[PDB]
Amino acid sequence: SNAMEKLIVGKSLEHQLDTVIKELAPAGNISYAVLQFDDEEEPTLIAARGENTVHSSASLIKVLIMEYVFHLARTEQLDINDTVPLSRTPRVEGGGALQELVGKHSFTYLELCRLMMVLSDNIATNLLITVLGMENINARAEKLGVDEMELNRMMMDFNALAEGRDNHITAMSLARLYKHIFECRDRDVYGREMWNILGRQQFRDILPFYWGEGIRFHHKTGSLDRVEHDGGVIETFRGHFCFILLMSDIDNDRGKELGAQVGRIMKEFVEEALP
Amino acid sequence: SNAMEKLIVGKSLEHQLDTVIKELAPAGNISYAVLQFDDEEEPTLIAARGENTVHSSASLIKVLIMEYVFHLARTEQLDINDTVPLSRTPRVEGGGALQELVGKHSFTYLELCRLMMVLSDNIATNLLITVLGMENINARAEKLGVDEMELNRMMMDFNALAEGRDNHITAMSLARLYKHIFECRDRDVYGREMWNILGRQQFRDILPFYWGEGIRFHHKTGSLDRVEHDGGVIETFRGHFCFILLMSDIDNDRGKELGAQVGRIMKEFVEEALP
Ligand code: NA
Image (cartoon, rainbow over all chains, first blue to last red; front, side, top):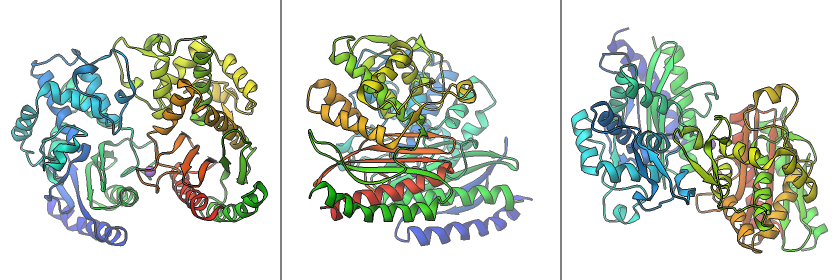
C-alpha cells in the first residue's frame, strides 16, 4: 500500500485509541503518533492525536542527550570510553543506580548513556549534561530538526521547574529523533549501540505491558507527577513501527493502565490489520 | 484490639482478597499473609492464604542475603565499606545496573546490598553469594528460624533450574524474616540501613501500584517466567503491617494486575477497617 492507503486504514486505529482514551482518561491531555519506518524513506504516518502539542518531556529528553554523545564519538570529538567522575554533579534522587553509590567511582560516556537510558538514571543524565553543555545539546536538536524538544533544566531541579524552566517534547519531534536513530542503527558501531541500548530498556510498565518478555522494544519511558510517557520502535514481521504516547494531566496509575491498553492496540493493529 | 478480635475482623479481608483472586487468577497458585507488627511482640496474623506453600523465590531470597551481610557487619566479621571487584563473578543479565558496566569497578558490600535490593541487581547478588558462601547464607536462615527459605542457586543459573535446584520461599518464612528486620530497625546503624534500603525499593508495579508515590513501603519484589511476588512492611497511622503476596503459575501481566488490586485492598483494610 502507498502512504495514503495506510493513512486511510489508520483511521480505524485512531478510533480505537480515542475510544479507550475517552473511557479511561476523558480529562487527560493525551497525544500519540504511530508511524511506519523504512530505511531511507520518510516515515509514513498511520495514526495521530495531538502530535504537535508540547508536553513536559520528563525523562524522554534523555534520548536526545544519548544521540548527542554518540554524535560526538562518531565525529571524534570525544572518546566514548573516556571517564567522568561520579563527583562531577550533585547527587539527585528520582531513580537510578548511581544514587545508591557512595565511593569514588568513574564511568565512561558509554556506561553513563547506558544507565541514563535503561534505568532512567538521573545522576548519569546530569553528569552528561554537566560535561556536554545544555546549549550544545539544544544546538544538536536544532541541527537534527527536532528542536521542539528542549533541554532547559537538569534532572530533579525543582527550583527550575518552579521558575518556569522545564524540559519539553512533542510526539512528532520525538518520532523524528527516533527515525534519525533508526537510520544509524546499521551504519556503524555507535548507531548500533544506540539501537541496542534502546532495546535494553528495563521499564516495561507502559506500552509493552501486555506484549510478553520476548518482544523487544526500542524505547524510553518518562514519568513525573501526573505525566506518563513511552515512545520507541518495534520490529515486527510487517516492518518497523514507531509508537509514541505522551500522557499529561493524568493520575500516574491511570496513565500506566491506559498506556498498557494503548500499546496492545497499537501492536495488534500494525501486525494484523495494516497492509 | 486483641489478636483474636483482629483475626476475626481479618476474615473479611480474606474474603475480599479470595474474591479478587478467583476473578483474576482462578487457576493461579496464589499465597498471601497480612500481619500486624509491633515492637517486641509476636506478629499478629490478620489474613492468610496458602501461607506455608513453597514457591520459587525469584528474587525474594535477596532479603536473606542482605540480612546476612549486615549480621556479619554487626558482629565485626566484615567491614561493610570493604570492596569487592565487579570481576569476581561472571556477568549475568535479567536486570540491574552492573550488567551495563564494562570498566574496572569495585563496590562496597553496602553498595552491593543496595543495588541487589532496590533494583534487584543480579550481578550484585551473585557477587555477594560468591564472597559470602551459599552454605553460610542458608545456615543464617536456620539460625533465624526461616529456613523454609533456601538459597540453592545463583541468579540466572539456567542449568540449576533444569537440574532441580531452585531458590524457595514461603509467605510465613518471609514474614518472619521481615519481623526480624523490623526488630533491628532502631537498634543500630546496620538495622537502620536495612530498613532504609527496603524503603528505597524502586519497583512499584505490584502492591503499591495504586498507593501514590508519597507512600513509602519497605519491600522487595520478585519476578520470573509466570511468577510475580511482592512483600514488605508498610508504616500507617494505625501501626506497621506486613503484606506478602506470592503468585505462581500466573501470566506475568495478570499477576502484576492482581497484585495492584490486592495491595490496594490490603492497605485500605488495615488503615480504615481493622481496629
Ligand atoms: Na505496571
